[PDB]
Structure formats: C-alpha cells, structure tokens
Amino acid sequence: VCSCRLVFCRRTELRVGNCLIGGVSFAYCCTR
Amino acid sequence: VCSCRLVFCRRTELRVGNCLIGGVSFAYCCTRV
Image 1: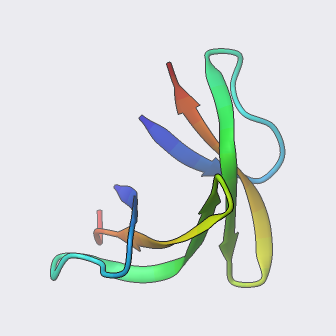
Image 2: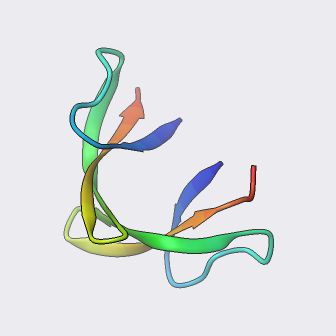
C-alpha cells in the first residue's frame, strides 16, 4: 500500500516517488 | 483510498493531483472514503 505523506515515509515504507496535490509536494511512500 | 493511475481516474474516483514516479506523471485518483 502507498500513500502521499507531507514529509517522510514510515520506517516500513520506501519513497517510490512524489505527489503534487493542491500546489503542495509530498513523498510518495509504499510498503515493500 | 488513492491510487496512481496512468491517464484516467476510475468513475468512482476524483482526480486530486499527480504522482511523479520514475520520471513519469500519473493522475492521483481518490475515492470519497
């Protein structure tokens, strides 16, 4: 499962890419 | 729930922004809940 997070991904997650929502950029974070 | 989809969201989803993965843009598509 993947989520856009404002700052860092979770310990259990890898930073797979980026999101752009309403002008704000997010880490795109997925569990492996 | 939100999903990163090439080109189109599903009819159950609203396009809220964009993903960028591996140099590629995707629509970021969310269901209401």
